[PDB]
Length: 504
Ligand SMILES: *[C@@H]1O[C@H](CO)[C@@H](O)[C@H](O)[C@H]1NC(C)=O
Ligand SMILES: [Cu+2]
Ligand SMILES: [Cu+2]
Ligand SMILES: [Cu+2]
Ligand SMILES: [O]
Image 1 (cartoon, rainbow, N blue to C red):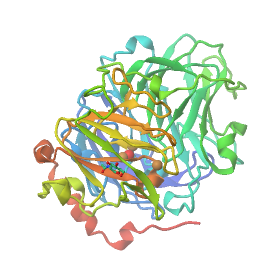
Image 2 (image 1 turned 180 degrees about the vertical axis):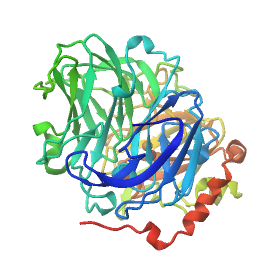
Image 3 (image 1 turned 90 degrees about the horizontal axis):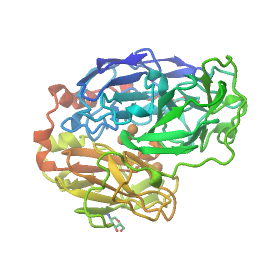
């Protein structure tokens, strides 16, 4: 089912069984993660009605529209503690924004705690009526979207120890090791046509190696940013990254396995495809309703992010020399006292959201809470951030709210590209020795989150806040009166309203 650009999103709890194990989950308009779609100039008005009442998972909510820059609408960006206070059970909040010409493949997810891990997440596609790559494919619709999701048999708040997915969900469906032969997702194609497949990771943690038996993947988009066409057999996708790839249905009519192998999971999930776990079906019209019997490519050409190149306005901003940006920041990641830190500080959410602190009179980073996690950025300048990998629990996929950035230096590469680098909004920091360097221009007044997108790391402190262009933040953003009321309502909630019932 589909949600339109002006619509209501009613959030409820119900039982779900995407892998044949039934447990309670979170539904949006009676559907597990429905598609949100519109056009690049639409004005979105999304009324989010929080009717959640199951105490085994988070009830208060906050929706993030991942990849949208939210210029002038920082109050609708959805990171609780930064842009808003949570929407409380029994209440509604109207988000109003526009893509402002930015087309691409995105996704929406709750930004509150680990609630998105329990299913409050889904694909969001913004179509371009002038798409630059329209000559490259014939079909692009609700049937060419492929979402990847990690799924747990117990509610996220009850996970004890290091999280390990029970299953990989492809378009909401999949199987777990030792589980029943639950229905697999089918992606239908016709021999001779070309399809713009939109691949989205909805993950709370695991990354996947994705490939389709017998077919190549011609990448033409990354994280809502178009690239020169670049063909590969297999790619590694991290939390919240998106790729559009042209699928050329040029093989014999047949059933082909679609494969998404996780880096971790219960009972051997990471190492097998046995019984159709970690799988979906690519079916050519005319093939029987049966399982594929194909096999993966033994020696795949692997996607390397430094091979991706931006199609439009390719050059990285600023002087084309490492360290020659207007503002040059280097962050030191750490893990101390059971908490991740950045430059010695572990992120903890303030009781007054940064945007509300700024609207209330804060004039500089020194006045903002929490102390040690907030970095001020000047207006209209070129920034270069460097975030060396090394810290445990990686690879850590960092994301920046409010901006897309050029990746002048990717993981696994020791070279810099200022002429043509891919532009994206979620980047892997790699492994020990890597020095991922990104660039962006500070053209979007407001407080924006910068943090690891593995939700278990975010909740243990791996986050910082950029207070960008503080002098123009009040003029640029003008939240509705309901926005400021969220905090009053939420601070007044009774203890039974936010209490988490654990399960074993
Ligand atoms: C943080 O710490 C590193 C290591 O001391 C230092 O080199 C870097 O300049 C610091 N970054 C910020 C933004 O303070
Ligand atoms: Cu996200
Ligand atoms: Cu991380
Ligand atoms: Cu975020
Ligand atoms: O996020």
